[PDB]
Image (cartoon, rainbow over all chains, first blue to last red; front, side):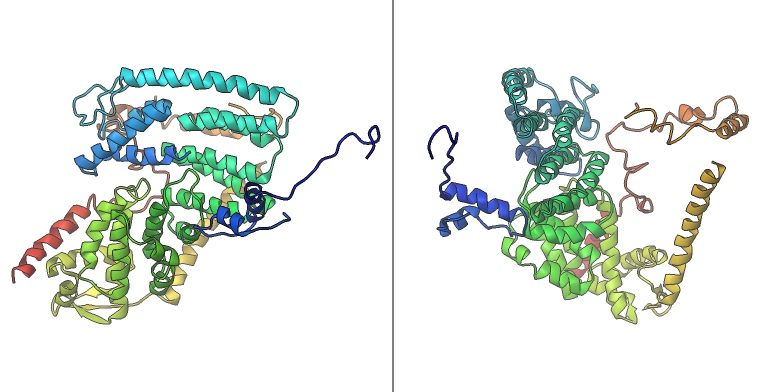
Length: 51
Length: 405
Length: 89
């Protein structure tokens, strides 16, 4: 963790509701849906904590 | 995006002499307004050419003559100001911005995407050639499979917009290979709805139908016509292709159709024609037919040209279904049920006998209609010799050319 | 109008001396000109310019609907003509 050893420390939070909708759409690009399914509402319902 | 399909529907009606004056000019206002607004002014040069001696034909780039009823063909200096104004601002901005994305140091994210950005502007204004060139550059360089299919759909749409089918035809055949490479069930669905439309333009309802049932459940509209429109299109294809029981499953008991109801003039009439075929109602079959010609086939941009083929087929279908069920009928009996006269019936029947769908002789002495059935093993025999004869032609002609070499 | 290299395009056909023979000899029956003689004389039909090419030489397959030129007006008139008698009985 000392400098001159490393050069970068990237931090990742878990998803936000906006971030969530994107992550969900990637998994959805590979399977079926039906009209009238809002990816937004499933982001709200999901409390999640992992992608 | 969304503006491109909706303008072209209305513009096609401007060409038609089959729609009422009222309707034609309801459309003509919508056209002119959204071309001036969104800068579809390069396409407007095409469209004057397309109206030209049907209705529209007084122009400041084509034929001078007073048999025009349309003023929405005619140029304006207001239109010419609009062209120039919008073109110069947007273009100027977008060329210098794009160039820098490709300039700076990154060729897999930024350079690929910038070419999409040129492509949106060409696709917006309806210049086909220069949209095909830019978007070629994106495809050529290496990117996601999903993006590769998606970009390619836009090019296909430009053909659909111009009302030129050979252009579409070239595009979706290429896309079709890339579908299993991405493994995307989402963009297989979006592929299906596109292919639906391509099959629809040319005469081939058989493939149209398989895809159109699929397009009711799933599609999210991406430069394609409403789901009201697609629902209507599914109904029409449904009657043509499928027998009584499959008509029942796929159309009538469709959760999709049931849940969209009848909210437009064209859907209202078509759903009525499906039910009456199924119910062995015959009185209301001929009235419903006249209404679907006016209000479904004509306002289409794909079944306005297949109108003649379609109306001839359903007429043949209804007569067929009654005969298939009945060994004997009277001309008077059959004619009461349909609501036409006896004389009017006899004509339409005797027209369709040599076309071998109806399979019935008709006596004039007693007025009985006997129903023969020579189709069976004998039927399959005529088909085989005929297709085999053709195959033989192919074998000799390809063969002889090569043997010479 | 050429695409790629000319190597692929020499590999997909080299013109035959046999074809040279066929073409000129046939031309004796074709008179002085009979390649463009008929569409020169008839002026390619005496009709409106329009914008479709699905009347003759359609892209889609030819199905017979040349029989009736419009059987939709006809079916309308037939239905309406019975309509009267029926109703007024």
